[PDB]
Image (spheres, rainbow, N blue to C red):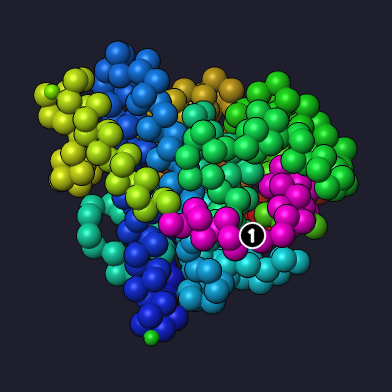
Amino acid sequence: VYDAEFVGSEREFEEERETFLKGVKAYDGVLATRYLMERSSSAKNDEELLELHQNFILLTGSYACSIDPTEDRYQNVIVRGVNFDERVQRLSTGGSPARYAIVYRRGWRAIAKALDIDEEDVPAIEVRAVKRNPLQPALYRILVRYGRVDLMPVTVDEVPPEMAGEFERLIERYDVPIDEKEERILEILRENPWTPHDEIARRLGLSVSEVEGEKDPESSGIYSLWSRVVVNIEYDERTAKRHVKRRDRLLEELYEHLEELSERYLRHPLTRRWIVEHKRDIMRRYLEQRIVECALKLQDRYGIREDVALCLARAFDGSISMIATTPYRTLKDVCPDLTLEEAKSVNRTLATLIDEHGLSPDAADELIEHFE
Ligand SMILES: [Cl-]
Ligand SMILES: [Cl-]
Ligand SMILES: [Mg+2]
Ligand SMILES: [Mg+2]
């Protein structure tokens, strides 16, 4: 249920494969640094390691920005059964269905198939870091969706304050209009720019869909507001060029660094060779943490029964936001014991459509799938 066709030229194929494989290697660094951070307290409080982790988050984002530069190299990008070509074709600013997909958890599974990627196990690229993302997270995701290689920083030091804690400066810089709901979201982000979307939604009594919006200026929500801002920023090829030049060298340096640093914390240093060989373990430890955190939150903040909570957490790699924007049928198919009541608690869109607007679950599910 994760598919895409590569429809570019052979030259474009080698370009895309190279970008993707570098992105996978960068994301492996996110996973390997997290592995070390979770295995050792002295490593987790070592600033040198935390900077490595953040720098890998940036390079992953940068490489993801470079996917499908011509916005025509892929066809029928389907993630968990949902066709993103159809999604992106409707939007006022259009764009790449491949990059649109990569910002969703497991989007990489479609693109990896298209590119025949077999160079390592579970060749993932995820661009959804929140906690320790050096950028304001929704902005980071929007840069990826718009292919903004020019704007995505390639080192933590080089993150502009306006893309992080001073994010409100970037919004003000073009005096884009902000809707009332968006202003409510910005209030929460002032308190912590890294507040997760599910929490913003819970705190405002809104659905996750309402908090997020479409990734297009014409919509309403944090993705929509950042899209509004970013389309006003002229594309800077000179800076994109600089970023592309440096990032490949930086990627090597981050790995060399990680290996060195890991030697004083581990009996088995995190060499690139070791990371590739133990990729499945690295990935599964990363996911297990997210899954259990998610399950606990689902049961305590949404009233979901313990077993269903763990089932949903597992199916969606620990993303409450994903769960909260998924059709009822899709959730039930993976987690049979889920009740409609429970689904309405986590996906408030379902509650609004069925309870307030009087749609059948099936009609509600059509809208949630096609239009999210
Ligand atoms: Cl599949
Ligand atoms: Cl060619
Ligand atoms: Mg919701
Ligand atoms: Mg050692």
Ligand 4 position by quadrant: top left
**Residue 59 in view (yes/no):** yes
Q: Nearer the viewer, residue 354 or 147?
A: 147
Observer-nearest residue: 261 or 23? Answer: 261
In the image, what residue occupies the spot 32% across and 59% down? 21
The answer to whether 279 appears left or right of 166 in the picture is left
| CB of mark 1 near ligand 2 (< 8 Å) | no
Which corner quadrant of the image does residue 269 belong to?
top left
Q: Is residue 105 left or right of residue 18?
A: right
Q: Quadrant of residue 313?
A: top left
Report if residue 311 lies within the magenta region. Answer: no
237 lies above or below 168: below
Q: Is residue 352 visible?
A: no
Q: Amino acid at mark 1?
A: Asp
The secondary element bearing badge 1 is classed as loop
Can you identify the residue that label 1 sits on? 236
Compared with 85, 281 (above or below) is above
> Which quadrant of the figure contains the N terminus?
bottom left
Q: Residue at x 38, y 60 (%)?
A: 20
Q: Residue at x 55, y 58 (%)?
A: 240
Verify whether residue 233 appears in magenta: yes
Q: In the image, residue 341 lies at what x, y percent?
A: 62, 35
Q: Is residue 350 left or right of residue 106?
A: right
Residue 26 x, y percent position in the rendering: 36, 47
Q: Which quadrant of the view contains residue 318?
A: top left
Magenta range? 219-245
Quadrant where the image shows the C terminus: bottom right
Q: Main secondary structure of the magenta part?
A: helix
- Please tell me whether residue 368 is drawn above or below residue 318 in the rendered image: below
Q: Please name the residue shown 31% across and 14% down the image.
A: 41
Question: How many marks on residues?
Answer: 1
